[PDB]
Amino acid sequence: ALFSGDIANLTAAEIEQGFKDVPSFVHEGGDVPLVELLVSAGISPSKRQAREDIQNGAIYVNGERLQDVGAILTAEHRLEGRFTVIRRGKKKYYLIRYA
C-alpha cells in the first residue's frame, strides 16, 4: 500500500528492522520521561550521563532531535503509539516499547 503521517518512514516493522542493530526494551505502559526510559532501556543508566544523553541534540527520538521531558515521554508521545527509536548518536539507535 502506502503510508504518510509522522513515523511513516519508521513504523513498527520499520523500526524493528530499522533498528535491529541494537537491543530493545519494554516498560509497563504509562508515560515515562525520555531520561528514565533510556536509563531503564540501557542507553545511558548513569543518572548524570542519562540526563545529558537526553538533554543533547544528539538524541533524535524517532529521527527528530528531541532533548527535553516537555519534548517526549513515551511511544504514544512520539508516534501514535507502537515503539520509539532513541537515536542517541553518541551510542546507537535503541528501541523502546511498552507492555
Image (cartoon, rainbow, N blue to C red):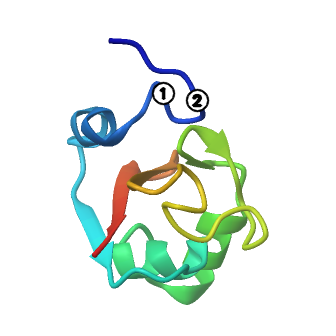
Whether 48 is drawn above or below 74: the answer is below
Q: From the viewer's perspective, is residue 14 above or below residue 84?
A: above
Residue farthest to the right, as pictured: 70
Label 1 crowd bin: few (<14), some (14–19), many (20+), radius 10 Å: few
Residue lying furthest top: 1
Other-residue count near label 2 (Cα within 10 Å), few / some / many at <14 / 14–19 / ≥20: few
Residue drawn at point x = 25 percent, y = 61 percent: 24
The residue lying at 52 percent from left, 82 percent from top is 36
| Numbered disc 1: secondary structure | loop
Looking at the rendered structure, the kind of residue marked 2 is Gly
Res. 70 image quadrant: bottom right
Figure check: 49 above or below 96: below
Q: Amino acid at mark 1?
A: Ala
Q: Quadrant of the N terminus?
A: top left
Q: Quadrant of the C terminus?
A: bottom left
Q: Which residue is mark 2?
A: 5
Residue picked out by circle 1: 8
Image coordinates for residue 68, horizontal then vertical, percent: 75, 67
Marks 1 and 2: in contact by CB < 8 Å? yes
Q: In screen coordinates, is 37 left or right of 50?
A: left
Q: Residue at x 31, y 42 (%)?
A: 12
The disc placed on residue 29 is: none
In the rendered image, residue 56, in percent from the top left (x then y), is placed at 70, 58
